[PDB]
Amino acid sequence: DTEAHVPDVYEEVLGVVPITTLGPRHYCVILDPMGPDGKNQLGQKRVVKGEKSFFLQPGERLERGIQDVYVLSEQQGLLLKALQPLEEGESEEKVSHQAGDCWLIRGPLEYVPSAKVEVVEERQAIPLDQNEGIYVQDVKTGKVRAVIGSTY
Amino acid sequence: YLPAVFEEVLDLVDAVILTEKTALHLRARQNFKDLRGVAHRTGEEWLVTVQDTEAHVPDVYEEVLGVVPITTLGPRHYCVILDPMGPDGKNQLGQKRVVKGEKSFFLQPGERLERGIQDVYVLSEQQGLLLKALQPLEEGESEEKVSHQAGDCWLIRGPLEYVPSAKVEVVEERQAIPLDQNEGIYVQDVKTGKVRAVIGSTYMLTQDEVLWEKELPSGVEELLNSAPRNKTR
Image (cartoon, helix red, strand yellow):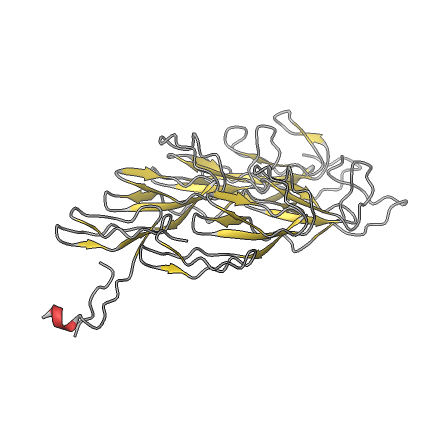
């Protein structure tokens, strides 16, 4: 609009905001962002990622700032608890996670925790060969399986 | 210049020195048109080099922010430019563009190197680059043409050179292990758990392989006949 704005007599300068830039591996959780109406939707939080760079608009604030992107390998996971239901189109999985159903996302992918979901634990894989395993208690059904053989 | 009745003479501003080694990074204080005939806004930061004017006089409409030396990439070098412009001439912040191949450019206003000019990644037949794809869709990134997903650890090995794209990230070096026949390394394929005990030719761990410990029931001193055994091979 204007690269050199003179503080008008009708304007009081509250401050100058540096540009908040998200790297190619980064996301931020904007607390209280506007919608299209230009009005602060307080309480809400919008996860923004993808090499974007914006200005912290008046009223907006970052939840915990620019932290990192969640990166998991074949041996790494993200045990997530869906603090909001209806995770239908949130990611490519297309499975509609309900409110709070703990579900483990694993594999060669990258994750950005949406406002609905929340990370619980890291869930590092355990290496197991044949005639060796880990006593696993499926706490959803109790049954201890003692899975052996391949890694689990 | 004979001053007029009204001209209060200020300091004599000299033209800054612009060789191809350097570029003058300045910010315009206000709208104007430079000597070359380019409209500039009230704070747009741009670069003037030898290609436009080899000796630029700091204009009254311009404040000199500084002079930037040319950032040159050798034949074996790459740099990760944080916040580079696209074709629009507008700083695409957050992004990072890997630049290599004997190139030499100027750090444009707003741009910055991630960790500077480090080195190119060089791996021999016994060397690898265990990479984790922090972004999915590594389809046309290199000659392999295999579309690595987001974070699938994959090992690139062989007589090649690698430049880690913005999407991918290096994890470890993965030096090869020399093995002859009747000797090997206990390899646990952590993707499937199965310990294979690969012997014979030399073997070096793939994307999903870790040395697996082999415990003996105190029956080791009777087979060795001070130095602890390598209980992983």
